[PDB]
Image: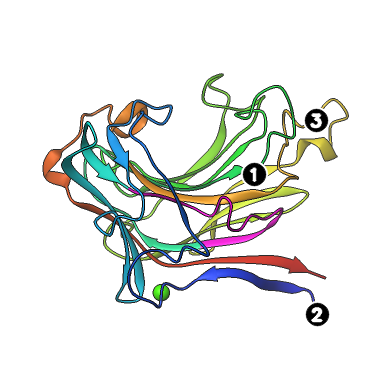
Amino acid sequence: RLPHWELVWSDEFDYNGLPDPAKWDYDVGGHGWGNQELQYYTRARIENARVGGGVLIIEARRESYEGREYTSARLVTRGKASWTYGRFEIRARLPSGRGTWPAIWMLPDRQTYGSAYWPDNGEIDIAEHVGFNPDVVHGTVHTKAYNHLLGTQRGGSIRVPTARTDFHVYAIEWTPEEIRWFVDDSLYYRFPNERLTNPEADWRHWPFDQPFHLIMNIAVGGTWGGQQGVDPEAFPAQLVVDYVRVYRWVE
Ligand SMILES: [Ca+2]
């Protein structure tokens, strides 16, 4: 073989209707999602997750729903597809609006490393954006030693002037040695596997040698998305996804 990124999973959203149930499941609930978020993430609701016109729209809606004043979708490949290492691309246009918090990210299939699921086993934030600070995209990792609870999370950012007007390929290349974040293949952050350079480094610093699945949502408000409040006029807000593509590196 020639060394190259091999496509192993993708959704080009070339169909019509609900997110393909073979590739996508939903996170459902309005319990705050650990962030005091205001939305109810709905299941297979076309208002919140619809495919058409060559794209997926994850849509945040201001509406009275199951005790919540907003609905949204948190689309996951959990239980459908997960990967250990790879190049992960999500071509998306980000939603606008103070109170919006679109995320493209990953969580571990399993609690391999004790004694909690999170952050012990990690979280790879491929692209995070908050409406009250438009155009700035964050790539971030959370691990037992590096997480937002300890204030020790590791990530970078990059201003994407046309994030909310145009599509941008948000990508990580996650390998045994490091995670690299790209916007349109602008490398704006990388997270080295400290286990390979530091004998005292373990899963607490690099848990990313286990299968992660992809998540895509728009949170409404909560700790980060809504510390400037939630602009109700910012709705409906759309996270529009041209495609999700996952590659594995083959040598
Ligand atoms: Ca597409």
Tell me which corner region of the image, top left, top right, bottom left or bottom right, holds residue 209. Answer: top right
The CA distance from mark 1 to mark 3 is 19 Å
Tell me which corner region of the image, top left, top right, bottom left or bottom right, holds residue 44. Answer: bottom left
Residue type indicated by callout 3: Asp
Q: Earlier in the sequence, mark 1 or mark 3?
A: 1
* Residue at the disc numbered 1: 109
Q: Earlier in the sequence, mark 3 or mark 2?
A: 2
Q: Position of residue 71 (x, y in %)?
A: 25, 43
- Between circles 2 and 1, the one closer to the viewer is 1
* Residue at the disc numbered 3: 202
Q: Residues within 10 Å of mark 3 (few under 14, many from 20)?
A: some
Q: Position of residue 3 (x, y in %)?
A: 79, 74
Q: Earlier in the sequence, mark 2 or mark 1?
A: 2
Q: Position of residue 187 (x, y in %)?
A: 56, 55
Residue positioned 30% across, 38% down in the render: 40
The answer to whether residue 220 is visible is: no
Q: Is residue 206 above or below residue 51?
A: above
Q: Secondary structure at mark 2?
A: loop
Count of numbered badges drawn on the protein: 3
Residue type indicated by callout 1: Asp
Q: Which mark is residue 2?
A: 2
Closer to us: 163 or 8 = 8
Q: Is mark 2 within 8 Å of ligand 1?
A: no
Q: Is residue 93 above or below residue 155?
A: below
Residue type indicated by callout 2: Leu
The CA distance from mark 3 to mark 2 is 32 Å
Residue positioned 32% across, 31% down in the render: 37
Magenta segment includes 79 = yes
